Image (tube, coloured by chain):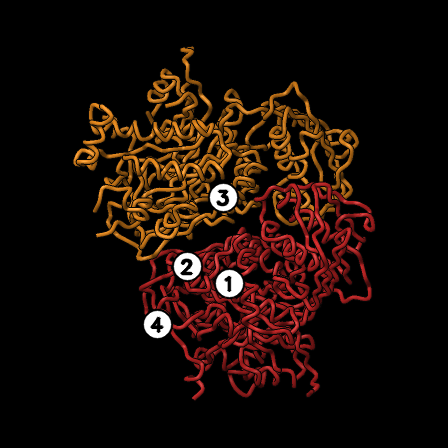
Chain colours: A orange, B red
């Protein structure tokens, strides 16, 4: 039983000792100054689950000790179970991840917000663990533009992320179908842009609508909170304001930003919009003002500008766009795209931030590559930093099985096993560096936080392992036994309603709602 | 500025001193042994909001002291701001409520789950407060049978309740349209009973359906958690399994429990069901087995059996019901109702629990009176303990204003001011005693936790004052200035999307969805 553990993500090295150390209600928590942050989080989480005081004690003297070890990487930790619980780390984030591994060692009741057990004693099996992340950037994107997620649910989603040792949350805040961020200078962004009349029901290709208004937004205080909440859990929040395309919500609010039409209203359907920004000095000024407030709220070194999916139809037919391309000396009207994003990227640079985009900038530019290995290596050749999120691998809005029993089926079949066997560009030594990978959850069809949970899990659990663990020890069948054996119980304890392995629960189904089924091989030939 | 405060519920006595005491990151929390429970909660809540350690110190020696004062009532506290923050209480619950009053004194940022402010210092104005509850039972009912509320949202709703000093949560767990509680002996209750094919859209009188499956359930561990979560906040959770009526979900699961029909399925519409339990030894045994598990999960001295709304049609036409009434020597088939509930009430008594019902038992029987003052005083004459929840006053599923702009309008117009001016039976000295009052939120039309928040607030804030505060100091116009001045900001900080005073936000509206509009005066004559 020496190599046996049920932890996910699996740690890099694990050894079991003999027996169990018992923790009573008197257990105290020590930490070195650098780790006081993680001490607070553990105290709050475990105190809630056990009803214990968990009062601080001098670090070397305590039941649970968090100790600084400068020879370890910052996100790396060592966990030792002895006469005491000793977690060594190179930094706060490391100590935090050690803490998570501890909670898993205590069992699922350690993840509840109030005690569900006796609390006379709990036991931690005696083990030695040594752990570090494989990738430094382990992401998830959350689309709150398509369906607004109430703040309570966002913080809960973030809590579940940290439990999987995911460090990046890419927050897609704006799109054709709504604008979620309150901007003080431009009140209509939320007043007008934060809601739509109705929503496509199923794929936009079925042309049916639900008659139900949808909307909401985060205030600046709400965003601050989310950022602070994530920071306590060592998650970086990268906001995205998507430009020049996916802009109809902003155009509805402030029509000057568009070409022209009857007044433009927040888009009620999915898919790609031919209606986009009119690129010009006024648009530019508008979005510099927006990015001024963004940068005040979000401390993140990257800020995402999107840049995906802009049809040139509007620009080609635009007397203004034509004029603009002449003034700049561009070859054609399509160069305005590169120009517009670059001007904003420059403004971000003025504020000390690198830019993040989906494709195609200053030095620290980060590309999120949804194309395959080729588009990825191509962006490295040019010196851009890369994170992989292939559309045919890592998109979690895509159906989890073949057939008609999955709710609103769209995209490729992307299964638990397929996702677990995924790789990021597997000696060319280029100027660009691979930061890591990210999973994207697009919200068109997920109209409640329950549906988002169904989409994200269990797959995101397997993905968290792909991002964190050692690729050498990878076997799907082995992973399953840990998933079903322990981890599903942890997800249940955290309030996450996932897709059961045998398929959707009857209340998770949505019959009569048309999806769009894609096949990756068919699209190649 | 000596009588001025923005606290809701308003405390019984309040005096402002001069200046502000500043709390730094070194602030420590002391408590007497009885209050260690509330010390833990404050530490968790305020630590989360400030990023402070809030380490324990000897009680008399600490920045925030929670001190036992046996001369105060258990739910009563005194709060003193000085060189230190001193909260005196007669018990844990008292200290808890003092803590809440403290958080309000620090401002809305104290209610966030992560710091949104500088945290260099916070200031508490120097004040003396003396406070007790007017009613000992201050309730809210939550219908999770009609629309299942995910666990994450339930705990958040409970957190918002405790902030208003509400001590009772009446959890309506089962109905025609679903059964939310997992029972180990009877797996189909959840497997079958926990979901329905679709739902009425609007009033059942419009006969239109949404085509959308709905369901979910709490496991026993989930319920335990909710009970423990509530207990940490001094909220009693009274579960309700409604019998003999509102039973079609249980009948779907186990058809023997009904008369007969094509197989019975979970009800898809609202309103009163003619399909009810067949009262008999087998039904009785079934529900004793259910109440055996309930009583293991919920520690509450009361357990609710419902008893509302049973049409006699089925029983009058039932050869079995007729036979049964003969065997017992009842006058007619309608006496089986009283008999069935009484047998279960007896079984509860065996377990040491009093019974709770909606109308019409052993000594500790509690009646929840939805009729007016008359039905209430009548139940006191008979010695039953009473809590008031008049249908024309305290039902929060009812529309908050006249007209067509309120979403799915149903019931009487029940406004913020009307609800704030409400009273419970205003020297007959009967055997029954008035425990308090309760507000009920029926979930037929609230299909998300957002909609539930819209229904419950701001009204539940005014109600919390009616239940807690002194009736002498009651003026609506004064209340408004506190509501708009401070409290709405507190609700925003806790993630609660309420009905704005000027009416529903555009994304809160639901046009095309038929309600049923009632007028209280018209129904009298």
Are the residues at dot 1 and dot 3 in contact (C-beta closer than 8 Å)?
no
Disc number lying in front (1 or 3)? 3
Question: Which residue position holds label 3?
Answer: A223
Q: Nearer the viewer, mark 1 or mark 4?
A: 1
The chain ID associated with circle 1 is B
C-alpha separation, residue under disc 4 versus residue under disc 2: 19 Å
Q: Are marks 4 and 2 in contact (CB under 8 Å)?
A: no
Q: CA distance from mark 3 to mark 4?
A: 42 Å
Q: Position of residue A442 (x, y in %)?
A: 38, 40
Residue underneath mark 4: B205
Q: Secondary structure at mark 1?
A: loop
Between label 2 and label 3, give the one nearer the viewer: 3
Tell how many labels: 4
Count neighbours of disc 3 (C-alpha within 10 A) and say few if under 14, some if 14 to 19, many if 20 or more: many
Q: Which mark is residue B196?
A: 2
Residue at numbered disc 1: B457
Residue depicted at x 36% and y 20%: A379
Residue closer to the observer: A50 or A278 = A278
What chain letter is assigned to the residue under label 4?
B
Q: Give the quadrant of the N terminus of chain A.
A: top right
Q: Earlier in the sequence, mark 1 or mark 4?
A: 4
């Amino acid at each position: 039983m020496s190599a046996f553990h049920q932890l996910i993500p699996a740690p890099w090295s694990f050894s079991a000792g003999t027996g169990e150390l018992e923790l009573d209600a008197g257990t105290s928590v020590g930490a070195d100054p650098e780790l006081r942050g993680p001490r607070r989080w553990l105290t709050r989480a475990l105190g809630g689950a056990t009803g214990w005081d968990l009062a601080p004690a001098p670090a070397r003297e305590a039941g649970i000790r968090l100790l600084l070890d400068p020879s370890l990487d910052a996100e790396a930790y060592r966990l030792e179970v002895s006469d005491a619980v000793v977690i060594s780390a190179g930094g706060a984030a490391g100590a935090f991840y050690g803490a998570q591994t501890l909670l898993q060692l205590l069992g699922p009741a350690a993840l509840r917000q109030a005690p569900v057990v006796a609390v006379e004693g709990w036991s931690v099996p005696r083990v030695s663990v040594e752990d570090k992340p494989r990738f430094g950037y382990r992401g998830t994107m959350l689309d709150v533009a398509r369906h607004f997620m109430p703040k309570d649910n966002v913080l809960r989603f973030i809590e579940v992320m940290a439990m999987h040792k995911l460090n990046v949350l890419h927050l897609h805040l704006t799109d054709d179908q709504g604008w979620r961020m309150q901007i003080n200078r431009y009140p209509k962004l939320t007043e007008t842009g934060a809601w739509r009349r109705e929503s496509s029901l199923g794929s936009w290709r079925a042309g049916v609508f639900d008659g139900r208004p949808h909307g909401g937004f985060y205030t600046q205080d709400d965003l601050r909170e989310i950022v602070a909440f994530a920071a306590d859990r060592h998650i970086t929040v990268i906001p995205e304001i998507d430009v020049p395309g996916h802009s109809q919500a902003a155009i509805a609010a402030y029509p000057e930003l568009g070409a022209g039409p009857s007044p433009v209203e927040v888009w009620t359907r999915w898919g790609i919009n031919e209606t986009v920004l009119e690129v010009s000095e006024t648009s530019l000024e508008f979005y510099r003002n927006v990015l001024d407030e963004v940068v005040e709220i979000f401390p993140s070194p990257w800020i995402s500008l999107g840049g995906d999916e802009v049809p040139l139809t509007q620009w080609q037919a635009s007397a203004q766009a034509q004029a603009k391309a002449a003034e700049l000396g561009l070859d054609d009207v399509s160069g305005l795209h590169s120009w517009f994003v670059g001007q904003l990227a420059l403004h971000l640079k003025h504020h000390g931030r690198a830019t993040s985009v989906w494709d195609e900038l200053p030095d620290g530019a980060l590309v999120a590559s949804w194309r395959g290995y080729e588009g990825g290596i191509d962006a490295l050749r040019k010196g851009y930093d890369v994170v992989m999120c292939p559309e045919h691998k890592l998109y979690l809005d895509h159906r989890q099985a073949d057939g008609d029993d999955e709710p609103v089926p769209v995209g490729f079949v992307t299964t638990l096993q397929a996702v677990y066997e995924f790789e990021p560009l597997p000696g060319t030594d280029f100027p660009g560096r691979l930061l890591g990978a990210q999973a994207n959850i697009w919200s068109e069809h997920l109209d409640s936080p329950r549906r988002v949970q169904f989409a994200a899990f269990p797959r995101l659990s397997a993905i968290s392992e792909v991002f964190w663990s050692n690729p050498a020890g990878r076997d799907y069948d082995e992973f399953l036994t840990r998933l079903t054996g322990a981890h599903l119980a942890r997800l249940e304890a955290m309030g996450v309603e996932y897709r059961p392995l045998s398929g959707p629960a009857p209340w998770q189904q949505r019959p009569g709602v048309e999806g769009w089924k894609r096949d990756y091989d068919a699209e190649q030939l």
